[PDB]
Image: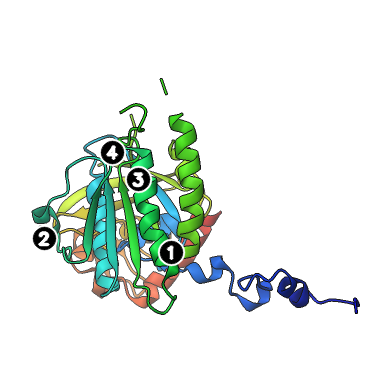
Amino acid sequence: HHGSTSITDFLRLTGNEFASVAQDGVTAGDISGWVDSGSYAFNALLSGDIYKGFPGNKIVVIGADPSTGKTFFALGAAKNFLEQNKDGIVICFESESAITKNMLVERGIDVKRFGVVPVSTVQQFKTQALRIVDNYEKQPKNERQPVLFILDSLGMLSTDKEMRDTRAQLIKAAFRVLTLKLGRAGIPMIVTNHVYGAVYASSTILTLSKATGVIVTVTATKSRLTKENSKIKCLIRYDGGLDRYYGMLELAEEAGVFKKVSTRFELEDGTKLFGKTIMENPEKYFTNDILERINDYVKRKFCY
């Protein structure tokens, strides 16, 4: 009965319907896909590719000084998600009391597809997030709408006890199970954190620092996908989104696609324009052409 066996046959013996030969390109990784942040430059820092964004089934931590606008950063990502996925919903697990209908309506966020779950402890967050995820997981893959989770914020969750403590151990356990269950379910999660247990939330930790809306530096403080201490600049628009183009001039320069000659920038054909002019109409100057070339440089700077 027991002769020579291919890798295909050995994988079928597991009885695991999702086991696969890498040649078939159907790993959980292959199939997770990407959630466009709405910013090309932010997409680059995350995934080394302006066209990708957040891993479709993973947790990313965004840390900053309080009042830096992490909340508005995550709402920016939520706004692009709800536009690109007309049936997608956002569930925000909120430990502060900041989110209001008016804040969301003014930032062009559809308030019929944005939910708010007030939680004050690690145990309440874990239980209530998993009650949603466990339901979503039961549904046939065919019935499921796209879902984005936000946790605002991690460091403001207490523990049933505290309400020096157990806290570290509760967070490690909770994020082990969430990481597994979000990963299989295909739900990405943004986790905000005041910086003055994040190490358990994700292997990708980004820092915002300050300096139409608010400019931040985004640093890859810890990253699986791109080189640590990598930096882009990103614009959090007052009208809600992460700006599609802001930060791309800086990249176009170091990409050498726009040479800086004097008080202005040179293109391939020879044209000389002010930065302010390029950025006042970026659809004209950031053509499929220029974006491809910038993207090739992004692969090199951000992955190596």
- Kind of element beneath mark 4: loop
Mark in the foreground, 2 or 3: 3
Question: For this rendering, which residue is in front, 275 or 148?
Answer: 148
Report, in whole angstroms, how far the alpha carbon at label 4 lies from the one at label 2.
Answer: 25 Å
Question: On the picture, is 273 further left or further right than 130?
Answer: left
Mark in the foreground, 4 or 1: 4
Question: For this rendering, which residue is in front, 38 or 56?
Answer: 56
- Kind of element beneath mark 2: helix
Residue 245 in view of the camera: no
Q: Which mark is residue 125?
A: 3
| Visual colour scheme | rainbow
Instruction: Tell me the quadrant of the picture where the C terminus can be found.
Output: bottom right
Reading the chain from its start, which is encountered first: label 3 or label 1? 1
Report, in whole angstroms, how far the alpha carbon at label 3 lies from the one at label 4.
Answer: 8 Å
Reading the chain from its start, which is encountered first: label 4 or label 2? 2
Q: Amino acid at mark 2?
A: Val
Mark in the foreground, 3 or 1: 3
Question: On the picture, is 118 further left or further right than 208?
Answer: left
Q: Which mark is residue 105?
A: 2
| Residue at x 33% of width, y 33% of height | 158
Residue 35 percent across, percent down from the top left: 38, 65
- Kind of element beneath mark 1: loop
Residue 164 in view of the camera: yes
Residue linked to disc 1 = 56
